[PDB]
Every structure is written in C-alpha cells, then in structure tokens.
Image (cartoon, grey):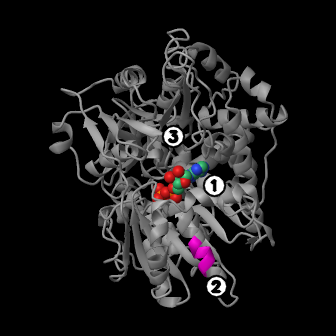
Amino acid sequence: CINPFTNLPHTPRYYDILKKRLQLPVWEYKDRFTDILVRHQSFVLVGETGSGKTTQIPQWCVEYMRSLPGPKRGVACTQPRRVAAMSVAQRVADEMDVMLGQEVGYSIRFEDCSSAKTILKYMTDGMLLREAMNDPLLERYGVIILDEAHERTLATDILMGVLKEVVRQRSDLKVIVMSATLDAGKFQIYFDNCPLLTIPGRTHPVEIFYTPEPERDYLEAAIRTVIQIHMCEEEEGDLLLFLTGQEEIDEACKRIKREVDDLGPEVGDIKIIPLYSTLPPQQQQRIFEPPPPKKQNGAIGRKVVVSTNIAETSLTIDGVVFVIDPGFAKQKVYNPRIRVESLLVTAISKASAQQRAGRAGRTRPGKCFRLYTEKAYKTEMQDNTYPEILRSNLGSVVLQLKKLGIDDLVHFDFMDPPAPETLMRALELLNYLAALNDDGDLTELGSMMAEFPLDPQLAKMVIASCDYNCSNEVLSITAMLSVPQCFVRPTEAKKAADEAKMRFAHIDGDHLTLLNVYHAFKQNHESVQWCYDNFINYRSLMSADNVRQQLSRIMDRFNLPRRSSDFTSRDYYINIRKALVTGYFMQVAHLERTGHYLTVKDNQVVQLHPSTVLDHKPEWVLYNEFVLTTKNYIRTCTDIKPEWLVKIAPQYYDMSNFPQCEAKRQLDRIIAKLQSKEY
Ligand SMILES: Nc1ncnc2c1ncn2[C@@H]1O[C@H](COP(=O)(O)OP(=O)(O)O)[C@@H](O)[C@H]1O
Ligand SMILES: [Mg+2]
C-alpha cells in the first residue's frame, strides 16, 4: 500500500523491514496499547531491552496523531543518550520510509536534525526541558514519551515533574513513560496511579560467571576474557564488553588490534567496534554490521563491541551471546558539603549488573563473565544506584525550573526529592552569579542565562564578556570547553603529542591555549592534515566550530554584541582572563608556600593537572574542572590576579565570611590597600 507522508508507494526497503519488526515482542500488545492510549492521558510501558519499545511505540503514537481532527502535532520520545536518539531516528526513518530530518528526526544539544515536516522527534531529555523554556506546555507535541526512565537521569526526573504539572493545564496531551524495569521508582504511583502495560521478556537464560577473589587491573583481565571467549567457545556469536569511557575504550581497541593477530591466519577474525557518547552518526552505525565471514578452515568470524553503558539498556546489538562485566561506570558524584562535582569510575548496582547480563540472552542462551566475586554482588553492591538527582549539583536544574516559573522549590513534586542542602547550594551558586536575587527570584540576567544550553558559570561568562569587550574570544573558549578534549595524546607517543600541544601554549595557561587552537584551526581552513600535523582532534574542532555558530545565534537573538579588543594591546589577553573570572570565580586555587594549591573556600589540596601547559605555578589559578583520582587535580588552568577576584566577584570574596589561610591574608592586604586609609 501507500506511504501517507510521501503519497508514494512504500519502497522495497520498507517491506523487508516491516516483515522483521512485526515479530518484535511489543507488536502482540498493540491492541491493548492502543486501548489504554485512547482512554487515558498518561500511562506506563515496561519491557526489557530489545522488546521493540523505542522503534515501534512512537510510530504507533504517530498513527494515533494522524487519527486526530487537525491540530496536527508531533510526537516526542526522549532518550537519556545522544547515540541512542541519533541512531534510532535513522532506524525509524528507514522503518517509516522517510528521510532522516524530514518526517522523522532528532534533537541533541547543538545538533538539530529536523524540519517543518518533522512529526516524530527523538531527542535527549535535556533538549525537551530546553524546549519547555520557550513553550511551557510543550504545545508542539500531542504525545510525549520519556524513554529509558529506569536510568533516572537528572533531566528525565525533572521532565516527569514538569509533565505532571503540564497535564493539569492540558487535556489534549498524552504522556507515556517507558522503562526496562519496574524498579528505579514506581512511576504509576507518581502519575496518580495510571495504567501499566508490561511486555514479557524473551531473554534466553544467561550463565553468570565470576572470579575467585577481587580483580585489580580489570582492563587487561577483561582483555583475557575477550581472548579466551574468542578461542575456547565453539558456536558463533558476538562479544560485548563494558568499559567506563572513551580513552580506556580506545586503549582496548588499539590494544587488541596488533594483538590478537599475535597469531597468523589460524584463529577466527574479529571486527572490533567502539561505542561511546561522542561518535558521529556515520560511525555510530557500525555496531549494526554483519561480523566478518568464517575462514575456510578456522574459527568463527566474530564481532567484538567495546562500549560504555550505552549498550546496557539504550540499544541492542543482534548477535551478542557473550557479555563481559568489569562492573564499573563513569558516574557523576557531588558532595553537597565539599561542593565539588566530578566524573568518577565506581561500582554498578545489582539492577545494572543484571541488565548487562541480559544482553547476552537476546539471541540464544549466553554467558556473562562478571569480573567480581559473589560477595562483591550479593553483599557488597547496591540493589539500585541512586537516582542521578541525588548525585548532582543542581545549579543548572534550579535555573531551568526558575525559568519555567517555579518559585517555591520544596513545594515541587520531585519523584525523589533532592537533599535540601544540595538545593540550597544551587540557590547560592545562582545568587553568586546574579542569576537569582536574595529572595531566590530570577533576574533579567538569570532569565537570559537560562536560554544558553550551558552550565550557569559558562553562561554568565559569555554574557558578561560583552562588557570586557572580548565576547568573540570567550565564545570561542566556551565552544572549546563544550566539546571533547582537543589534544590527541597516543600513549605510545606522549612526548610528541605534548610538544605539538606546546606549539599552541599561552603563557597564562590553558583557556587561552584553547583560544589559540581554535584560531589556528580556522585560519588553516579546517584542514584534516593540519589537525594530524599538530595532534589536534579534527572532530573536536569541527564540533567546537558548530557549538560556536549555535551560541552566536543566541547572542544575536538577545542583542549581545560579538566583539574583540585590539590584538596589539596588552588588554586583549587581560580582558579575556578577567572575563573568565565572571563565571569561574568559585573555581580558584591559591599557591601555598609549600608548592601545593589549596582551593579558595573549601580548602582542598590540589595539584595542576599534568596536561597543563603552564610552565610555572601561578600564585592564583582559575580552573575549569576538578578531577578526582588518587590525587585531586585541577584541569584547564589559567593564571589570574587576586585583585580581580575582589573587584569582579566581591559577593563571593567577602572577607567577613572567609576561612583563615595564606589566600585570606593576601586578600586582606589587597582590600586594605584599595581603601588607602591610615587609621
Ligand atoms: N539503529 C538500528 N539499526 C538496525 N537495527 C536496529 C536499530 N535499532 C534497533 N534495531 C533492531 O530492531 C529492534 C528494535 O529494538 P528497540 O525498539 O530499540 O527495543 P527497546 O527500545 O525496547 O530496547 C532491535 O532489537 C534490533 O534488532
Ligand atoms: Mg529503547
């Protein structure tokens, strides 16, 4: 029959895919799905990964929208994960026989693939909350679906609160909450005891393996699980290994590419595939590829995917029988008393481990090779990881809620309410940035900050830089800070990489070094060869350029001038460094007489991250990032003048409320000197 959007026949592609997708677990419940949808404003849908929730259900809601009178609106389906949203959009575009970016599309922070024609949009949970800023009832959508709500991300929880208020003012909107599990909060009690639909699992049983006692270096000891699986096992099937991020991942794909062809033609081939947050579409889509063929003589031609907890629940790779679970992941941590946010590798929950093992069972029965003991699972691990709202600084969150018109914050319906101390640190942060007044009301400046898709600190820095006549350079720095690490540092060629990085070093430090990289990238015409020559990440730089363009359009909308100072003047670099202070004045460390650094209020001993270009230890350093390892590192570091701290951020540098230390004694000396009294 006929494609309703194109008014043409559906294609050969379309029919081949329709055939396979009708067989997905979700389809036998479509009638009862439809029957709940037409009768209720909101309900919950639970089903294991691979059951067909993300691809099929939003199509059904499109079908539903096309049944309706003429207020002709979209469907939104939120993903916690960029790679999930972008790759399902491509998949669903194919399933619906449409062009990605036309009837089906996606929206990620700085990456909008959509048009006038878009009626189904796969977006991050973060982006839908962004859209609510300018459209508080989300009138562009008739159906909104929060997918992967079991991952309890910060943006997902806030969307559940928001949408629960939206449904009281809008009768025409439908909300669906989809999840892999019934745990991670109860959802239907939250949405006023609304219907539940559960899709049975087709998990081919999975043999859970362990190790005798605690493993120390799991990277190489999970490589030795990857190898022994790719010889000892006799039937076909692909491998999925859970690492914690995109260096450790790339390590294990550089490693295990010369090895394990340590071995001639004899053993079976391996198509090795990495998966992490950053990858562009054209290379996300290689997890969906057929493994290499069987050799005439030898072993199974096999596929190994090396991946973040993106593959835990957010998608399925067909072919996977063998799952290796190191049992850690890059979480977000936040002490509300230390006031330090950082990304930390840490032990997963029983919920999570069991999810990861689940992936091995999605074709035939499989084996999960968990690299722990039963004691490090049964007795030593949590049932459920804390929902992300209890592990984050809520500065951005609070600003977004205030921009959405939410005044009283304890009188706000969180599913799991945050510790009221973390809430109050967020209010203070925002008051220090002048985003909120002393009553906690949104200022004109706060309102504007909220429409930049940036941490409040960065937003304030961009806006305030106009008054230091260096908005152009601050926008470039901001864009470099908003994309992945730009310096390629192969572990086999550290001195070479470091020396290339030094070609760009500014004497006052790393922020200006990022400005130097960006300027050099542009004046060399976005050249890939230039990037290779200088060990600069071409993808990072292309991403930065795109972020800068996006941020530029926001500046134009708000009439904030995009200006530079005179490069021949000394004020050029001074002005930019003063601008950094307007946003980062709380991220400041003082050089002690001992050669250590102590963070300004919280008195934490830190050292300059070893990747810094700084030649010397500035007396005062402003930093972008606090890195928790076995040492505290401050990363992306600039030399600043303490006088700037007093002049630009007096509310924070209030000596009546400040701990005794070398920093306070210099600061008091500076404050007395400004006042030039002889009492
Ligand atoms: N991007 C893609 N490319 C090719 N095939 C896919 C893609 N995404 C999903 N599939 C296939 O279609 C199925 C649909 O699964 P999905 O809707 O993602 O399930 P759930 O969201 O419930 O985990 C998968 O099991 C897989 O076999
Ligand atoms: Mg899904």
Seen from the viewer's position, the closer of residues 370 and 133 is: 370
Image location (x, y in percent) of residue 488: 62, 26
Pointer 1 residue: 91
Circle 1 — which element? Answer: helix
- Whether residue 30 is visible to the viewer of this picture, yes or no, is yes
Q: In the image, what residue type sits under mark 2?
A: Ser
Magenta span contains residue 438? no
- Residue denoted by label 2: 67
Crowd class of label 3 (few under 14; some 14 to 19; many from 20; radius 10 Å): many
The segment highlighted magenta reads 60-64
Q: Position of residue 577 (x, y in %)?
A: 63, 42
When the figure is inspected, residue 363 is found, relative to residue 126, above or below; the finding is: above
CA distance for labels 2 and 3: 54 Å
Contact between marks 2 and 1 (CB within 8 A): the answer is no
Question: Is residue 240 found left or right of 90 in the rendered image?
Answer: left
Which amino acid type is marked by label 1? Arg
Up-down relation of residue 423 to residue 577 (above or below):
below
Q: Nearer the viewer, residue 612 or 259?
A: 259
The quarter holding residue 100 reads bottom right
Residue where numbered disc 3 is placed: 623
User: Could you tell me the amino acid type at mark 3?
Assistant: Tyr
Q: Secondary structure at mark 3?
A: strand
Q: Is residue 121 left or right of residue 220?
A: right
Report helix, strand or loop for mark 2.
loop
